[PDB]
Picture 1 (tube, rainbow over the protein chains, first blue to last red):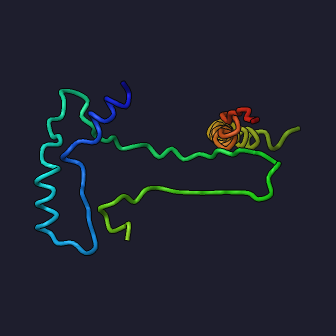
Picture 2: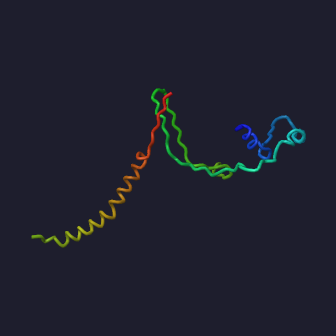
Picture 3: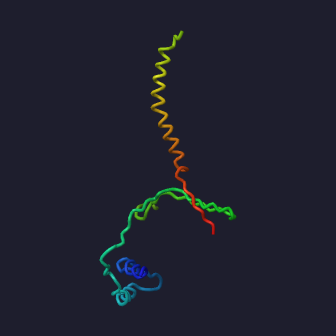
Length: 89
Length: 47
């Protein structure tokens, strides 16, 4: 039931990208997608359309003290740049 | 007996205002730097 609603809600047609690189043309791939992918979905159901929420960077620390290990692993991270802004660059 | 009584109570008034205006802020800053270890929380992971 969970996987059925998962596939009915998430792998929808207006959010998936067929990407193909290498030795192939564009009209060929477009026409194959018109034959096979056309008829997939796009009729999204009535309720719970997926839309993000701006998630809260809390900022804290967690330490798993486990002294039966040879080496130590530390990661430290700060605030998010995003995607569209050139602060990423 | 006390040639300094006037000015010592003047400085007593100024010290009362200083330690009423300052000492709550130092207590706030103490609680703000001890604020992490008041809220730290443990959990027990063995295999």
